[PDB]
Length: 258
Ligand SMILES: O=C(O)c1ccc(P(=O)(O)OCCO)cc1
Ligand SMILES: [Ca+2]
View (cartoon, helix red, strand yellow):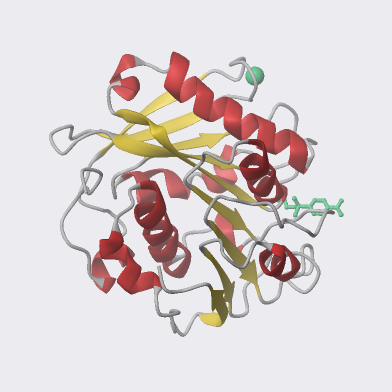
């Protein structure tokens, strides 16, 4: 596997606040075409090969600040992280899906050479919080060539996603009453194709805003899903299959083995 980056993982090494790669950043003007700009976090070491990329969208009326902690956390494990702002703070889930693809296209076509030369433009993912999570599902319908999708406590009015072809990892919050898992996160996951590689993780006692503050249980398995599907790295299947039993997890569902 030519996309394998970093040493062989352990349960502690995926919980590490800093991975094996150092992080540099680039700021992108809000007048970039198709999205509201953002901050790119990328690994600085080039001697192991180029990296895949994930665009990170925020929720309704939120900004990249609410998703900022993913930046260094994930990119230090060998990914290019693009925390973006939306065109307006009121953008709908469909609008946030189009803007996630616009951010990924900016990385490929127009990003700074320091970023371009570290990027594998064929290995791209999407991630989003709340309405940005509903945008992550919309992004995979709009671009089924993406490698992974991670809706965090997602909110969407449309509950059926039976045509999704991108490995999707949904994270729900037990005490979410803004996008309750019983009418949002769980219906989305169960509607995903039975054959798709997918997973659902419900955090115990978590609120709708748990993705906005550093969370090891979120971090360790966001990194595992991204390595497993953006890097095709089967060294991270051990963490995902069989289903994790972390004390922080109150409900886990998957289509293991993968
Ligand atoms: O209008 C509603 O009912 C409504 C429902 C959910 C959201 P959200 O994107 O999950 O909020 C999280 C942003 O930090 C916004 C509005
Ligand atoms: Ca713009």
